[PDB]
Length: 38
Length: 55
Image 1 (cartoon, helix red, strand yellow):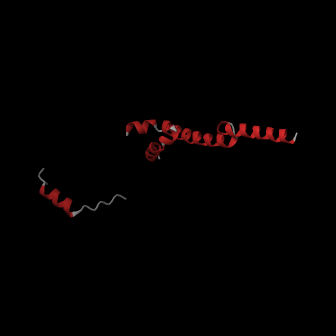
Image 2 (image 1 turned 90 degrees about the vertical axis):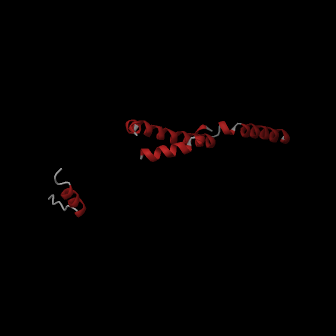
Image 3 (image 1 turned 45 degrees about the horizontal axis):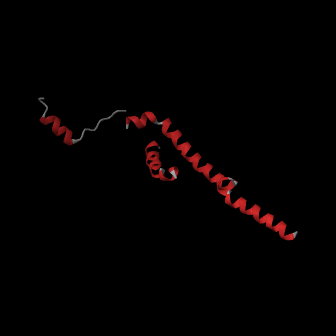
């Protein structure tokens, strides 16, 4: 009876247990240009 | 004499039926299997104690 009542818990537990070219996007360029002084 | 033999047989069979859940290999085998599954599960849990603790 104890083994049967623990089946759901076992399942949950089991689930847990188991050349660098840089293209910088415009959005980032725009940010860097706006904050260029900083 | 014939009645006596059959009566004994009946008595024996009745005794066997009444104690089968704890004595017969079939029923005992099923209990073994359920116990082995849980063992394995617990072994696994103990093996991953660190990760589980961190989580």
